[PDB]
RNA sequence: CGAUAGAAGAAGCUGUUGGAAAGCAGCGCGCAAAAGGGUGAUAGCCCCGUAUUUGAAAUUGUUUUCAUACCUAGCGAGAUCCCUGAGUAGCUCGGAAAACGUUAUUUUGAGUGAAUCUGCCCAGACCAUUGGGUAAGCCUAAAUACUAAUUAGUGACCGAUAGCGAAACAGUACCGUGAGGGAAAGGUGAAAAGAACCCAGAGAUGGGAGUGAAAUAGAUUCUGAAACCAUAUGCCUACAACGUGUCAGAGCACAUUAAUGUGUGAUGGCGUGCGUUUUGAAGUAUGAGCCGGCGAGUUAUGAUAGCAAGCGUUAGUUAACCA
RNA sequence: UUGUGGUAGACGAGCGUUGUAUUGGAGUUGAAGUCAAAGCGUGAGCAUUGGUGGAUCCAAUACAAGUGAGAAUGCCGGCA
């Protein structure tokens, strides 16, 4: 099996197996979002349980 | 390792054929029709065990009802008198008495007729 | 334990040999033994079974009949699996492995327990070079030896460290008994023996191998 | 155990094999567990991993991570940790002594780094390319010493 | 040292069932031979062989020794002179090779075009420092890839629908103008001793006789299943509405894996098949004329999880390869 | 004591076929096959006897599968 080249470059793993990710809606069209929204989307997050199983076998 | 089927299919097929012995023509010759008839016959046998339990009760009730009408009493009141007198006897044995032992069956009807309940 | 020598005449030596306690193990492992026997039984498979799949069988890659308007059913080839010509769907292949892996320490533990249970028991006598060369290479002498030792029906196994030739010249026409070097005996050869004759220096090599 | 009676440990060898084609009595007949007439019941299989039926998959929806050192490899380091080095038995920890203890391979030239905070009782004499300030503080709080090779 | 024919090569009788002993039993014997095949059943000692020791006139393979051609040889000094692969390396315009979808490196269809050890190329655009290497000339064993064929052998491979399409005279019969497509079919008995002769018949053939242990082993030739077609003991059936059965039930006829037995079923109650796919099928939806054989969750390489075993806190475990 | 209708489906426990490895056993005084019968099991299934048949087969514990046929307007052969 080959690791998907798109699964990597977008999902980093951690010590306990959580898959770190970046928030979307942070590429353009900045004036259409509030500074609260922008500063909340700047921080990183983890995949939800609904996607953890699908990303585990993808990596 | 090429395992080849022989004596496995034939034995389990001949069991079904043996069960469907005494059927009409192909229903005992061909394995397929024999298997269908055995399953259907098993269903019939299952249903008729239950239906036998009910039908024989009905026949005993009919015979007992008739035996009472010759003496002027009805089935609906005979069972009520039986309950009030605490007498507990199957309608089967009661019908067997009325067919085999007329004198003793008449003795039971005489006691339930008039004697004080309990 | 009391491991005692055997002479050529079948009589026992009056001097028993003491045994170091490292050979015998108070703890016995049976699962590693079972796995060792299974992997010995495996790798004995030649695995030369081969079958022709649907594409490999010589036949016509054309449609026999048209797809529609014929009273017959749809068919795509004359060498399909459900055809008498015969295309075997899966079939045995000559690329199967049949091999299994067992850890080195697990094999050592299996060998340790099997030596422990086979040793310090009946028909586990000690043997030397004298009767290994007193055989003279004639199997009649060895038949007499087994008859005297009452090991005729037993599957006696000779464990040898120096590959004596007179002993190997005999015991070769005997389908029952056999002789092996210490680096050649395995778990299965050890517990099929039902009886074995072990050389004293073989026994010395055994404590060393176990470590 | 003999060869005529050989047994595995219970619940180790044999487990219930799910045979998918042999009759309905096993609960795995006819359909064989695929369901009923849909894509997952055909011979093809279960589509592609990560597919969402045409909707943009999760990875295609999220931004890509950035690699600052493009085309480079992180410099690997051999790290000696203080919480476990106490369990190891040796004094005057240099590269050669680690080779004899086989913590490091003799065919490796990676620089040695010292890491850790856990207090150690006996003194050790390290020969490390890099050492933390507080790891050095712990080592020198005991009667040990550390020399920084260059 | 082998290859292409070969020579020698040990060890058993008696009795019993049996057509026949080699089986079985008693008493023995040989083995560097207990691999195998045949011999009237299942033979270490009946035969051929096998282990082992050997042998080539002639052709041919490998290796070694000797001689003999051919090639093959070091370290300094001075001179400051000469040579070191040109339409070549670069560069431009279109393509490509490399993991790369053209880009440092390699290559080229069109055009242009250098320098000469203080020289030229390279170290992912490029420049400088440092370092590495000597393009535009050629040849190169070994480890590597494969088996139509020859010899020996093996198989938890197949055993006439299987195994090569082809166990038989198979790429045949046959189909097509042609390329091309492409079958089925094995077994008497130890030994033909293959049935002389008689009877019926025109004859094949059949019934006896004869051979044979067996002829219901007879050339239709090992065993002979079901569907299918006929014959017969016993029971029932010509006023009867039937998914053909089931539960009760007389009478009739027998006697068993001895069992409140078996075969048939006048009559009474109840009763619209099996798979598929559907909200819903007795179905005026679908699939099967019947019987028998074949016919669909595997293998290789990895990942996760459950269970179990080995080894354990500077642990655990090898891959290729060698024996 | 509470329970035991059941499709898709999940889980657990077993039967049967062929072969291999260890043990033991039967067989021309008749093995497999094959037919019949008024047997034994909760189920896959398993025996006993007799006829035919003429040489291999069975039991236990493990292992490996071309391992289970009623349907595919399924293929082949035979017969309605
Ligand atoms: Mg079948
Ligand atoms: Mg084939
Ligand atoms: Mg189910
Ligand atoms: Mg499923
Ligand atoms: Mg659907
Ligand atoms: Mg379907
Ligand atoms: Mg579905
Ligand atoms: Mg869309
Ligand atoms: Mg000779
Ligand atoms: Mg001879
Ligand atoms: Mg023989
Ligand atoms: Mg360049
Ligand atoms: Mg390319
Ligand atoms: Mg230079
Ligand atoms: Mg650079
Ligand atoms: Mg040059
Ligand atoms: Mg064929
Ligand atoms: Mg045939
Ligand atoms: Mg022609
Ligand atoms: Mg005749
Ligand atoms: Mg015929
Ligand atoms: Mg015949
Ligand atoms: Mg009438
Ligand atoms: Mg009328
Ligand atoms: Mg009506
Ligand atoms: Mg009616
Ligand atoms: Mg009726
Ligand atoms: Mg009706
Ligand atoms: Mg079905
Ligand atoms: Mg529909
Ligand atoms: Mg509809
Ligand atoms: Mg209708
Ligand atoms: Mg229609
Ligand atoms: Mg349809
Ligand atoms: Mg139809
Ligand atoms: Mg059929
Ligand atoms: Mg696991
Ligand atoms: Mg249930
Ligand atoms: Mg078996
Ligand atoms: Mg028989
Ligand atoms: Mg199959």
Image (cartoon, coloured by chain):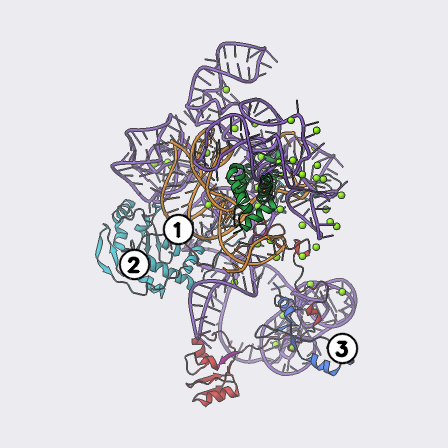
Chain colours: A blue, B green, C cyan, D red, E purple, F orange
Could you tell me which residue is drawn at 53 percent across and 53 percent down? C96
Judged by depth in the image, the label closer to the viewer, 2 or 1, is 1
Secondary structure found at label 2: loop
Give the letter of the chain under mark 3: A
Could you tell me which residue is drawn at 73 percent across and 76 percent down? A25
Q: Is residue E150 above or below residue D148?
A: above
**What is the quadrant of residue D1 in the picture?**
bottom left
> Mark 3 near ligand 8 (CB under 8 Å)?
no
Where residue C107 is drawn, which disc sits there?
none
Q: Is residue C205 above or below residue E155?
A: below
Q: CA distance from mark 2 to mark 1?
A: 21 Å
Residues beneath discs 2 and 1 located on the same chain: no
Give the letter of the chain under mark 2: C
Query: Which residue in the protein does label 1 denote?
Result: D4
Give the letter of the chain under mark 1: D
Residues beneath discs 1 and 3 located on the same chain: no
Q: Identify the magenta region.
A: D76-81
**Where does the image place residue D53, in percent across and percent down from the top left?**
71, 62
Q: Is residue E229 above or below residue F8?
A: above
Judged by depth in the image, the label closer to the viewer, 1 or 3, is 1
Name the foreground residue: D65 vs E255.
E255
Specify few, some or many for label 2: CA neighbours under 10 Å numbering under 14, 14-19, or 20 or more: some
Secondary structure found at label 3: loop
**What is the quadrant of residue B74 in the picture?**
top right
**Where does the image place residue C158, in percent across and percent down from the top left?**
32, 53
Cβ–Cβ below 8 Å for labels 2 and 3? no
Query: Which residue in the protein does label 2 denote?
Result: C120
């Amino acid at each position: 099996m080959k690791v998907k080249s798109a699964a990597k470059k977008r999902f980093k793993l951690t010590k306990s197996g959580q898959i770190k990710r970046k928030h979307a809606y942070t590429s353009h069209l900045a004036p259409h979002k509030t500074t609260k929204q922008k500063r909340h989307l700047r921080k990183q997050g983890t995949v939800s349980a609904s996607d953890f199983k699908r990303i585990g076998n993808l990596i | 390792m090429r395992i080849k089927g022989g004596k496995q299919t034939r034995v389990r097929r001949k069991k079904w054929l043996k069960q469907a012995s005494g059927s009409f023509g192909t229903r005992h010759a061909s394995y397929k029709v024999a298997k269908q008839t055995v399953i259907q016959a098993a269903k019939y046998a299952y249903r008729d065990r239950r239906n036998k339990k009910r039908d024989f009760r009905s026949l005993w009730i009919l015979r007992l009802n008739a035996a009472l009408r010759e003496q002027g009493m009805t089935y609906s009141v005979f069972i009520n008198l039986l309950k009030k007198h605490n007498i507990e006897i199957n309608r089967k044995v009661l019908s067997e008495l009325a067919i085999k032992e007329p004198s003793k069956f008449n003795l039971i009807v005489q006691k339930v007729k008039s004697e004080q309940p309990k | 334990a009391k491991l005692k020598l055997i002479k050529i005449d079948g009589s026992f030596e009056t001097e028993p040999v003491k045994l170091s306690p490292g050979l015998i193990a108070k703890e016995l492992k049976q699962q590693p033994v079972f796995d060792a026997v299974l992997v010995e039984q495996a790798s004995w498979r030649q695995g030369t079974h081969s079958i022709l799949t649907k594409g490999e069988v010589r036949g016509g890659g054309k449609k026999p009949y048209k797809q529609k308007h014929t009273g017959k059913a749809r068919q795509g080839s004359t060498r399909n699996p459900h055809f008498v010509g015969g295309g075997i769907v899966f079939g045995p292949k000559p690329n199967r492995n049949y091999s299994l892996k067992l850890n080195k320490k697990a094999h050592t533990a299996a060998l340790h327990t099997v030596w422990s249970e086979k040793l310090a028991s009946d028909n586990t006598h000690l043997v030397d070079q004298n009767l290994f060369n007193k055989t003279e290479g004639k199997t009649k002498v060895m038949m007499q030896f087994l008859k005297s030792a009452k090991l005729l029906d037993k599957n006696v196994l000779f464990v040898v460290n120096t590959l004596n030739t007179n002993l190997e010249q005999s015991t070769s026409n005997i389908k029952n008994v056999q002789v092996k070097h210490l680096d050649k005996v395995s778990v299965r050869d050890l517990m099929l023996a039902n009886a074995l004759l072990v050389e004293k220096e073989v026994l010395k090599a055994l404590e060393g191998k176990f470590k | 155990m003999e060869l005529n009676q050989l047994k595995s440990v219970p619940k180790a060898r044999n487990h219930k094999t799910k045979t998918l084609g042999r009759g309905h009595g096993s609960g795995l007949g006819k359909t064989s567990g695929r369901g009923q007439k849909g894509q997952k019941a055909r011979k093809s299989g279960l589509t592609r991993p990560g597919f969402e039926g045409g909707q943009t998959p999760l990875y295609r929806r999220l931004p890509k991570f950035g690699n600052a050192r493009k085309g480079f490899l992180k410099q690997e380091w051999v790290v000696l940790n203080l919480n476990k080095i106490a369990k190891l038995k040796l004094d005057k920890i240099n590269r050669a002594s680690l080779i004899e203890k086989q913590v490091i391979s003799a065919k490796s030239q990676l620089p040695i780094k010292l890491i850790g905070h856990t207090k150690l009782e006996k003194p050790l004499h390290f020969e490390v390319h890099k050492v933390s300030k507080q790891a050095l503080k712990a080592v020198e709080n005991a009667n040990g010493s550390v020399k920084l090779l260059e």
